[PDB]
Amino acid sequence: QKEDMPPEHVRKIIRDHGDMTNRKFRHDKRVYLGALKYMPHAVLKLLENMPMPWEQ
Amino acid sequence: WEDADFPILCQTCLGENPYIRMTKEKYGKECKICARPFTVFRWCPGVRMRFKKTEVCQTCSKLKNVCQTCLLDLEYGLPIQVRDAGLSFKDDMPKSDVNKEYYTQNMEREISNSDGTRPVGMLGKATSTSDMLLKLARTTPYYKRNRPHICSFWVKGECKRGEECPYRHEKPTDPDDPLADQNIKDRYYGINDPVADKLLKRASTMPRLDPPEDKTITTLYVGGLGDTITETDLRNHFYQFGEIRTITVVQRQQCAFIQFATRQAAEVAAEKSFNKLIVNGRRLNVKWGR
Amino acid sequence: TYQRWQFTLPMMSTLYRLANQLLTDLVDDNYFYLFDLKAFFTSKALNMAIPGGPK
Amino acid sequence: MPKVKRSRKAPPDGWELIEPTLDELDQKMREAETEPHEGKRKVESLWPIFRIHHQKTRYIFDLFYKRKAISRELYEYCIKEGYADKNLIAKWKKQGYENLCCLRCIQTRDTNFGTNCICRVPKSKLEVGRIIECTHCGCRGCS
RNA sequence: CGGCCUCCGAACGGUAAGAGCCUAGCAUGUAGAACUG
Ligand SMILES: [Mg+2]
Ligand SMILES: [Zn+2]
Ligand SMILES: [Zn+2]
Ligand SMILES: [Zn+2]
């Protein structure tokens, strides 16, 4: 099976990449761009899992 | 596009182990020459050797019959210029862009009419194998084809990655050696190839039997026979090559003289025998008598 | 995987009482006499409007 | 301040002695998390996180099974509050896996051929000892 | 004792087209590297 990672793995990845202007990444550039086509799906999945005002 | 089975390249470029690890990536890249998108294969040739990759269009490779990753021929391993010129070949390789696209397309259609055994087109009908090219071939494997690059880090001292460096921690060749500038296009077309040009200066340093002056001197002096050489055996050696006008085997010299009735027979025979005459395992030397 | 619930009636009655203000306080269908679907389908098919209904 | 805790109920009565090491490890993980992306590397910048994760979880694995010094209810609570790692523990239960570097290095899909990464191979099988830092963890021979 | 209540904004369509030169960008991260009695 596929086992889950600790949250700091992704938190660190995203923090590192910041906003892709540093030249270190610069191949992510084109994959980052290619993932645009699926961005309206991430938004739908985000908004339908909204947290419901009786929860913090 | 192409979608195929496996890459054809020199066994030197294949590597040492009898079991290979090759991963297929469909339409992975465009040929450095053809720019046709072709399926690329990746292979790990050995431990701590750089991973090799299929490097040219399948059609472009079936055309010229070279190591589809090492760029060297599949038969002897000779660069295009040298192999062709020693085979007496003057090929019209396309260099134009539009004519190049059309040419690689038509050549893929011809390779489609071909059956996967012989190199398609003229590249086969020059199959008179040249001993100069044979002797110019590296007879043992040159696995230096997979030695890693230099790590600029350790080249300034900086490679603190340990032995995990993906480059050989060796002093970099100061670029001036023309062996550094072999672009894929240069090495493919075989034009302005200075490694093959050094190979050509070598082939000019390689000894053949230089012809003597007097057009009546058809006396070929054989050296290094031993006492186990027979007169009739040397006659059978130089027999089908033309008319042997006289045999004179000097046992007190371990030498001999074959007088020929045809100057062409004498010349072609000596040239075919130069440093290659092997009778009873003896390293026989052909010369022109005085 | 959180499908298929099963409750008891004490639960269901407390749930009912809490949801009491979001709910409709009628027991039957006679309220929606000329205000049900088939009434609105017929109204639409005849291009006439009910006092409180759609056009 | 702490790993602000979702369960809202009282952590059991063995929690206050595991507290200090846990917290200091947490602030430690925050420092290794913030250590910023200099000429460091990219493939090697996630290694400290797997160190400290393995460390957190090996700690709570000690304080339960090896010493028997924690109640099982406190144990499952420390699982639920993200101090422990369920699947790391659940592999560590197996035979050959005492020192698993992380859960991924045995995920076979992440490699092309569907085999574990060389991190898993014992050192005896090599017999040549070329130092290997597994790309995923950075580990050097977990088992 | 009947009720009857629209419309709300954006793009193109006008301010040219170029040939050249100059200089960061942007792509690669390559292939392969000497031979004797
Ligand atoms: Mg107009
Ligand atoms: Zn390991
Ligand atoms: Zn590993
Ligand atoms: Zn690991």
Image (spheres, coloured by chain):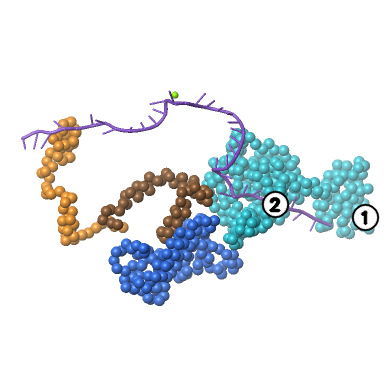
Chain colours: A brown, B cyan, C orange, D blue, E purple
Numbered label attached to residue B250: 1
User: Which mark sits nearer the N-terminus, 1 or 2?
Assistant: 2
- The chain to which mark 1 is attached is B
**Quadrant in the rendering for residue B60:** top right
Secondary structure of the residue carrying tag 2 is loop
Residue A27 seen in the current view: no
- At 52% from the left edge and 56% from the top edge, which residue is drawn? D38
Q: Position of residue D39 (x, y in %)?
A: 54, 56
Task: Give the CA separation, mark 1 to mark 2.
Answer: 56 Å
Which residue was labeled with disc 2?
Answer: B174
Left or right of E11? Residue A28 is right
Q: Position of residue B83 (x, y in %)?
A: 72, 45
Q: Position of residue B253 (x, y in %)?
A: 92, 57
Marks 1/2 in contact by CB < 8 Å: the verdict is: no
Task: Look at the image and tell me in which quarter the N terminus of chain B lies.
Answer: top right
Please, is residue B107 above or below residue B68 in the view?
above
Secondary structure of the residue carrying tag 1 is strand
The reply to the same-chain question for discs 1 and 2 is yes
